[PDB]
Image 1 (spheres, protein in one colour):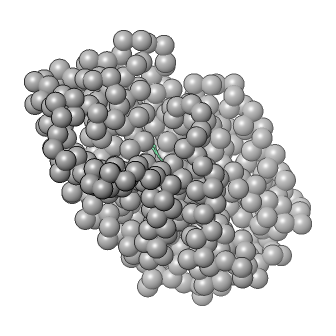
Image 2: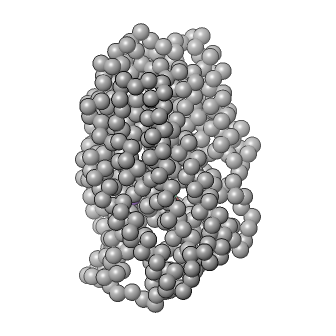
Image 3: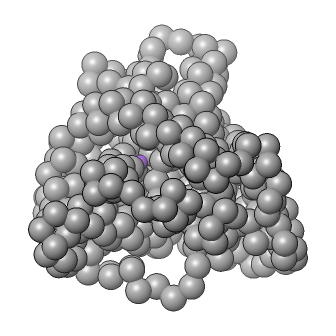
Length: 456
Ligand SMILES: O=C1NC(=O)/C(=C/c2cccc(Br)c2)N1
Ligand code: NA
């Protein structure tokens, strides 16, 4: 048995996130430093309004993906790590999942760093003392302790951060535009003086940004509110109501702040708003500086935990269920996380983001296909928590699914500027014949699937 209280399906009465609340999580989750860099650097290849469009477009494809990748977790309260067990093996899933937990972990050390930079700036603008690594750990530590309260803290922190972040940001735009003596419409076309990058690969850079979160949303959305006695058509509006809520959370948030990153770049030559606003205004008081840094901290806190730390936690406590618990998995993930020292990664994000999509594109495709197409949403919780059952395949690993991943990865390379969308679609489509083959050796359903509601 692989079950323990932390890695267990989430009972109907334990669910706490409705559609408005999930939006309140996503709005604050989209407000984060890294989108300044991406959308800023985008101004090299396109002008600001197009970048906003590449953001809105990229935000929207992510949501279309969320609608499908979230549907099993909402209905059945299960993990990401647990859910991968279906098409890949019970252990074979560890292969893509280790790929993915690493990614998740990479973002965690990056943002803890940005957070640390902020806190270190606040202090040295007071105490002149400027030690960063201590502030790194301390922040890593602070996130861990606030992550202990799982989605409960997250949900309360993001609803209050959201408007504050929203206001600090609208203010930010005012300060720039004003202090530069420029209208909104004027800045909107000042960019794009070095074309070459396809607009498709632009959209693909923002899609490739959230793909880790989108693919493994489970760990967030297994907490959303569901009515067990709906129907096919009431379940679909429910999925859609949640999917709609994520759109209204991440789009307007990442459009306003994407715009700020782009604006910074285009007005002053730097993606970092500290610099762009400081110059344009010609210095700022120590208070109003500290503010900005409180923002970065508030903006890092609203994104890092929920998006980067939750999912390796659940990966640990659910693979080694007697060794790790959620809280203990959080401690081990944040330590490993910081010991990856991701702040030394050579390059820029865009190409990395272009990497992230085409690396997990087939993974999202194989999971959507297994659950929706092959099995028709008809799953067995019982077998997901047991070493030997209908998800054990060949001695714990489903090599055919690992085969479909490779093949689909290959085909993905045949369309470099659309890598992600071909690899997903390829994996999606190939899983079907591959699974209709495996079904001749192994069963796709189980009698024990009637105990599903016992868990809930
Ligand atoms: O999965 C993710 N964890 C992160 O921290 C993260 C950052 C990010 C997301 C979208 C666009 C951009 Br630009 C950056 N993604
Ligand atoms: Na945030």
